[PDB]
């Protein structure tokens, strides 16, 4: 089979690999819709999680089952599935301790395009498939559902980590697709006033459609002073960090009230240290809790989030700015995320099969 | 002054009372907008919380300050305020351990029309005024803000007690005004599918506008069976009880998954015992958590919820089905709550003063 | 092989069964140390969870691995293990949402002697062995470690469900071996004063050694009145239920403060309904939270609790009042749990093998 | 009256001040037992929380009521009280939001020797006295209880912030008196293995008496490598930071597992930034939660912690290494904390009065 792979830090290329073996609990899956992620750009070109050889890239897919292991009981060949970016080993220590996304070690539930061949190939492998794949609801388009795999779950996790409460004033820093889903998540956790902070302008407007009330432009003054002015010096109740760099945490601490939460979901691609300012952190004692976490995954997470689409309560289509057909175009799509043109949010790649609707 | 009072179990009438005394931390307030509550109905006619004589009724008000104590620092004469139904003693033991609504004993933060003269009088008393009174935002109509005092905060509290998570399937039992607010609260905590259980048709359309997806009418049969059918036997994730009686808890237990929460905010007006069925409660071990709580109050709770009106994220006007003018009309309004026409959600009474815009 | 089985309601006896089949993730285990439980007593003689025929009893074992499946990676033949009473299916829905003890449905992680052949046989089966079996630390006697399987973990779980905070005054109702472990768990969650409710005198001294401060015997009168007197009417902060019957919950409600938690871990053997008194439950609004939960299990739970024995912080040996040798003596041991001499806390049965120290 | 005051950053001296006025909710209190704190050394000589003029120092006291305001209902003249270092304004926004220690702003519940005249004077003032003073139990020595005001509550808060669970392996970094109470707190929250990390050796031994199992000497190698070696590379479950500097956080992150908590209570006296290492923080995603908080205070906190002394479950006497008599000796005692001799943990100063036992 063909797949698009990382060939050591700094290089991608198409390669041929055998089809993965399918153990008793596993499933093999062919992609129907795929998206590329900014995370793969940090991983390939910044070496942000270390070196990899012949690793198929990608971790956002809707797919169709082409094989199941002997002990798979909930899935059959031909089933269409939402594939979560995180596919935990559910019996590992960290899963039993409430952190399945770190199953087998830090970030270990994130397999696809972390250390496991991902979804940018003709067939890919899923561990604990009964546990890790949700059936695609008949009322959701494959491209809408591909946004669940990572963008919705990660953005929403930012808002979960920020411990957002009913009527909270929230600031979301970074308004790419994960940030837009952090705004939506905060809205769905009951935030009132929501400040969206972008480098851009263009897609801070879409943030208003997901529940943002106030847009803050970096290219204007210091965002902290802008935020303190808008709040009459009081600051915000909670902060989600969904973009930026290692220096964004200091801004969050400076704009937030004492007794609060900062929820980071940004994959930090470079920099030795994240600096937290001693004074504005209440000299160690301000209860400004700092969290940084990898998204949940598995079937239940996808099922719960999918219900928001099915019930008309979340529109993920707004994130899709560019559409391609054919497995080859995942290369083109990943290069867009590397080069970041103006009107880009997320590309999606659809793949057609002649037995798409008849495979069994 | 005049006020409408409970004159022992089964009787109300107007009485004259002295204007209450104002201590250093207290405020005296006059009503600008008032609403009656079915709670006063249980208290008066069912004797649900014991006998009372000459206790002024009502605990839902937007008001205007007429006097402040010498130690009140945030408020002044003429300020217009949202009065929470619950006005805790914030330094009491129960407050220090995170339950201010029980300040000084069980239900002790619910003063107005529980054991303290309520808001249905020309002047009423607020303890710890700086802590307990939120300023009325200029962008909210008094009639909409009076829904914050109890309806919004109580219905939202049901959703909070039910521990609603993103994408959960929720059942709200009872769709009076509290119930509609439990649907809204559930929606604002991120619920997907939401079953609303009631019989009235307009309640069962406003509920859809607040985020209900599914309407369950008992006339179509046993509501548990209905819910189990609709969820292909798995049941719902979380339940909010916002109406019904002591037997509603068994229904909740029977329709909910193991590892779940039942959030009750219904004031139970009669019956010796709430029956929990042993087998369906997992013979003691089902992790079907049962919560029954009085609403939060105080200014912060009002400020936070008011922000949802100010930001366009909550429309409390849908709750108002009857409008009156003049203080004396709180009697007619309360009688609506007792006689219960199918026209009814919430009445509001508007009261004007010659110096409503000039008092200072 | 032979095993001691429930032969329908009201009868036990020895039977021959095939050695169970071992799948890729499973392990077969032989008992080194066994204990009987009053739970099997309710199951057999009261029919508390329905009828069963030819189901092998017991769910408390230290064991030795005799076979592993092809996909078992952490265990090998001859390894000695602590077997949790609860052995979840970790990838099931309920596990993914944080309730692995209900994997596959309510009580579904409690397999042994609920619906799956238990540990009272020459060989028994463990699903998801790598996840579910902890290695026996070399510094713990098998007889002490067998208390971890259910007694420690269940009693500690009562304390966890009761939401015990530093310095809380706690009442533990029922001071059998689970109850003594609820006292210990409460002590290990930082409780100060701890009332232990029972009638037996030695239970009411071991309880003092585990952190009880106050012993309450019903023979001195109504236990609620006793507790209210002892707390000058304010009542207790938190209650753990570890014994009694369906009527114990009302006692708990009556003796506890508003804004509190009642943590039940008692397996209720009979009765249609658990009665919660309306007035004392704050007419629905007292924030007296009611929790009823099956113990956690799996290896991590066993590892964590075992660490408390290894570090000198928990002495489970005090629980053991009767010691037997040989597998057949699990019958005598279970009959002790049924006939209930005042001598009794927990029996343990030790089973030896010629190759106990050489099997590999 | 005389008091020991901060006279601008860098200077202390004895000054004369009038006795404070006593408002309706206030109490005036004379000291019976006092302790100095390392925090006052950062505040005076490092200027760590800004400049102050004529501010009486100290915030650890047991005292006796000499005057009460007209609305004080729970205290009378002559009552002996445990005075918490934190005396919140319980109705302020932050208190209503669950953070009373930040009442009126970050650190605002910490009044004594933060910005309010403290306890090192013949008479001092307490706001909201009914809420903020606990009666001294008859079974606790004044000097034992002085350790509750700050040392026990802060150390225990470190363990609370570290989210310690039953059987957790914990590392406590910094083993001064706050650290020794963090070890005790972790023990009282159910930790198993506990590593105590000191610069010293002498009072790492006392740490074993409070539940530490392993001592780690800074003067030996890198504490992170020591800890990873002792845990077979697995690291610890939770970390409490109770001493050190801005660089201690990086050590905590490097020794802790993914999916975990670091609870800081160290008042950080200098340094612009606290550095968190990007890589070992899981490049933003390791769920290594970082918390830093000021202790709770008020009466209930003191009452709960005092119960641990009364019940024989906490011995605070072990912290007292030096004893003085007379109000003047608080100067001597504070200089010990500045200069830090070898065998010092905490000094205590007792003050005798001829009507100590007769004042009314
Ligand atoms: C699976 As990810 C770290 O790109 O959100
Ligand atoms: C203050 As109420 C019990 O009527 O919601
Ligand atoms: C596994 As059990 C209900 O006997 O503690
Ligand atoms: C009151 As303190 C910051 O010295 O623990
Ligand atoms: Mg707000
Ligand atoms: Mg005028
Ligand atoms: Mg451990
Ligand atoms: Mg051999
Ligand atoms: Zn390489
Ligand atoms: Zn991604
Ligand atoms: Zn009467
Ligand atoms: Zn009401
Ligand atoms: Zn039968
Ligand atoms: Zn058992
Ligand atoms: Zn100065
Ligand atoms: Zn201090």
Image (cartoon, coloured by chain):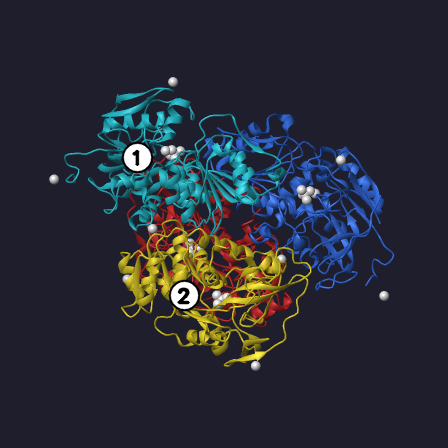
Chain colours: A yellow, B cyan, C blue, D red
Q: Quadrant of ligand 15?
A: bottom left
Residue located at (61% from left, 51% from top): C100
Residue located at (26% from left, 60% from top): A229
The answer to whether one can see residue A260 in this image is: no
The answer as to whether callout 2 falls within 8 Å of ligand 10 is no
**Considering depth in this image, is A106 or D36 the residue closer to the camera?**
A106
Dividing the picture into quadrants, the one containing residue A203 is bottom left
Q: Secondary structure at mark 2?
A: strand
Disc number for residue A7: none
Q: Residues within 10 Å of mark 1 (few under 14, many from 20)?
A: few
**Considering depth in this image, is C351 or A317 the residue closer to the camera?**
A317
Chain at tag 2: A
The answer to whether one can see residue A55 in this image is: yes
**Considering depth in this image, is B252 or B150 the residue closer to the camera?**
B252
Q: Pointers 1 and 2 in contact (CB under 8 A)?
A: no
Chain at tag 1: B
Dividing the picture into quadrants, the one containing residue A218 is bottom left
For disc 1, the marked residue is: B321
Which of discs 1 and 2 lies nearer the camera? The answer is 2
Residue D263 sits above or below residue D301 on the image: below
Residue D181: x and y in percent read 53, 54
Residue reaching furthest to the right: C354
For disc 2, the marked residue is: A320
Q: Is residue B7 left or right of residue B326?
A: right
């Amino acid at each position: 089979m063909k797949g698009l792979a990382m060939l050591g830090i700094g290089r991608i290329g198409w390669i041929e690999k055998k089809i993965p073996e399918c153990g008793p609990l596993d499933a093999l899956v062919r992609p129907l819709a795929l998206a590329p992620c900014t995370s793969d750009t940090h991983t390939v070109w910044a070496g942000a999680i270390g070196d990899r050889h012949d690793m198929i890239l990608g971790h956002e897919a809707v797919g169709q089952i082409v094989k199941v292991g002997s002990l798979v009981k909930r899935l059959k060949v031909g089933d269409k599935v939402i594939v979560p970016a995180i596919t935990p080993d559910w019996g590992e220590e960290e899963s039993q301790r409430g952190y399945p996304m770190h199953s087998g070690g830090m970030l270990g539930g994130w397999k696809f395009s972390n250390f496991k061949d991902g979804v940018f190939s003709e067939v890919f492998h899923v561990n604990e498939a009964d546990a890790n794949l949700a059936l695609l609801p008949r009322d959701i388009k494959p491209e809408d559902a591909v946004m669940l795999s990572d963008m919705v779950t990660t953005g929403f996790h930012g808002a979960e980590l920020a411990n957002i409460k009913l009527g909270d004033t929230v600031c979301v820093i970074g308004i790419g697709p994960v940030g837009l889903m952090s705004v939506a998540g905060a809205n769905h956790l009951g935030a009132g006033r929501i400040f969206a902070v972008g480098s851009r302008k263009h897609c801070c407007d879409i943030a208003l459609e997901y529940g943002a009330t106030d847009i803050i432009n970096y290219k204007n003054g210091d965002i902290v002073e802008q935020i303190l002015k808008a709040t009459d010096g009081k600051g915000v109740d909670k902060v989600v960090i969904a973009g930026g760099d290692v220096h964004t945490f200091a801004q969050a601490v400076k704009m937030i009230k004492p007794g609060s939460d900062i929820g980071n979901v940004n994959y930090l691609g470079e920099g030795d240290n994240i600096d937290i300012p001693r004074s504005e952190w209440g000299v160690g004692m301000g209860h400004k809790h700092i969290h940084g976490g990898l998204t949940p995954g598995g079937r239940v997470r996808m099922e719960k989030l999918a219900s928001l689409i099915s019930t008309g309560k979340l529109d993920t289509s707004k994130l899709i700015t560019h559409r391609f057909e054919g497995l080859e175009k995942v290369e083109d799509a990943l290069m867009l995320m590397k080069n970041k043109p103006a009107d880009l949010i997320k590309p999606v790649v659809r793949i057609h099969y002649d037995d798409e609707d008849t495979l069994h």
